[PDB]
Picture (cartoon, rainbow over the protein chains, first blue to last red):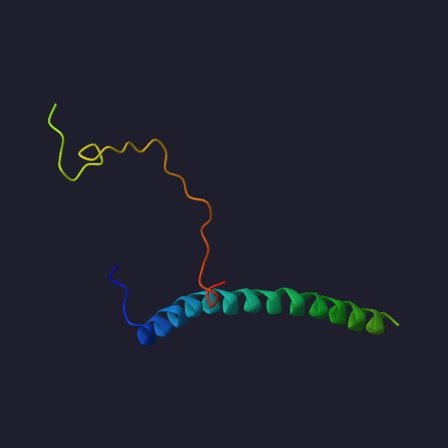
Length: 53
Length: 30
């Protein structure tokens, strides 16, 4: 075995967790987009109906 | 019919099967 010391092992684990968090941020951004767009569509329909009225 | 000294055949041992039971991640990665 050629493991690095424990102190830097913590940093190695942090780097792997950083990769996972990097993926998670993009996932949340796509979530925000998919959430926000339908609300815009609904507001557009609402203002169109208000104009008709 | 030469037997390498670092082989298990140099000893009286024969390995018939090697398998992995479970592969886990460190608790931070998990």
